[PDB]
Each structure stands twice: as structure tokens, then as C-alpha cells.
Length: 303
Ligand SMILES: [Mg+2]
Ligand SMILES: [Mg+2]
Image (tube, rainbow, N blue to C red; front, side, top):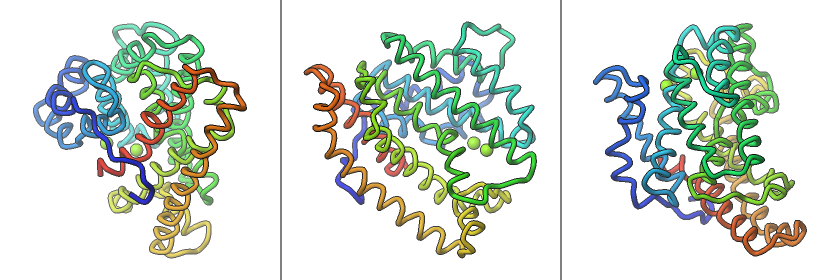
């Protein structure tokens, strides 16, 4: 890896991988043997075990379930639904409703799956934590509506800045990191979560994932005529070739990873600034190592 973040994987990964189909199957999310085979080919329990190496048993299963759900949910916007913000919001409203209370049994399977994840996610977490993580979920769903609006008007982004304002929410990294707290039964001190230093660290985590994702998905997205990929956007913004745009993105990933270390080195002083007590310093260290560092490296290793 470009910076010395250790590669990690939950020791309980084999069982979580072997049992991963039971949950989406029970919820109606995988409707056939063919769909199950397709799901296993994604390696989503493997991904979860790298984001959540500190989790085992039911806590790791929740992480596997979140990964499974992310990809099954995203599938629902592959076709015409993703081209229309009214149709996209019709679905995302039904899913996001789970944040406000129970769902009617007529709600779509993907909404019931979300509701079950969110129910488990909130267990043992402070009300203030649940409210914040719910806000992150609503940012995510609103981002899906914004993406469908762009597709509807055939209006792809013309700058990296405009693209990032949307993709930083649809990439789903912040809810992934939120789950790492729940999966580890800890909470980073809330005033430090809000800090400028931690905000920058999290933005790096989000950005590194979305940039690597756009490189990994480039050829598939080119074949579908997708225009909201950082490579295509940089070509429009700067006149660059796609080749120079990829190289720019690679340089940006490396530079941001190096900045991540710098920001990490500020955390001792940040803890002093916010007068963290002993338990709070321990919780911040769990967040740094088990939530932020893991999400930065987990997707890289998964590919
Ligand atoms: Mg898909
Ligand atoms: Mg899509």
C-alpha cells in the first residue's frame, strides 16, 4: 500500500462468507439460484471482513449484510428507475422511511432489508449517534435522487467539484464507517467526529474510495455511455485525455493518502483540544484504527 496502513481481515471471515446468503434470501432480495450465484461472485462478505476486521459473529454478519444490501440496492437503479428522479425518489423514500418508524409489509423487499440493518445498527448506540447516522443515510438517499436528476436531464457534471458534491454521498463510505463503530461497540467522541481534523480524514476516506471506484468501473461505465465518472468529467473540465485524467486521479489518491497520515498525526493534539478523558481517547483510537483506516484500505484489498 502507498502508505503504511496494515491490511486486515476479520478472523471470522470464513463463517461469515459461508453464511452470507441466509439474510438476503430471508428478506426476498435474492430470488433464484442464478441471483445467489451472482451475489456470491461479488465477494461482499470478503469486503465486509476487510472493512470490519474487529468484528466477528453477529457483528460481522451485520457488516456483511450492509455490503450485500448496498449492492442489491444499487442494482435497482441500473435500468429506467435510475434515469428518473421521481421514480428513484419513489423508491428511496420507501427505504428511508425505515429511519422514522416501522414499514408496512407491502414495502419493497429492499426497504425491509434496510429496516432490518438499521434496527440492528442502532442497538446499544446513543440517541445522538443514531440521529447522526440517520442523517448520513438521508444524505445517501438524497444523493441517489440527485444522480437520477442528472441522468434525467442528460446533464453530467462539468467539474470535479460538482461531481464530488454528489458522489461523496452516493459512494456510501460514511454509512460504512458508521457501521464500524456499531460493529465494534464503541462511539468516537461526538465533538471529535465533528472536528475539522476528523472531517478532513473522513473526506479523504470517502474520496479515495470514490476515485478508486471510478478507475475500477471505468471500462464497464464506458460501455454503458456513463458520463458521471471522474475520468469523463475531468476530460470535460480540463480538455485532458482519459489517460491523463486517470493519471491525475492516481496522483490525487496518493497525495490524499499522504495527507491522511499528516492529519492522523494531529489527533493527539486534537484529543487535548477537546479535553478527551481516558475512555474517549480509547474510543478515538478505535475509530482511527478500526473504522477510518479500515475503510481506506478495505476496498483496495478487496479488488
Ligand atoms: Mg450492481
Ligand atoms: Mg447506477
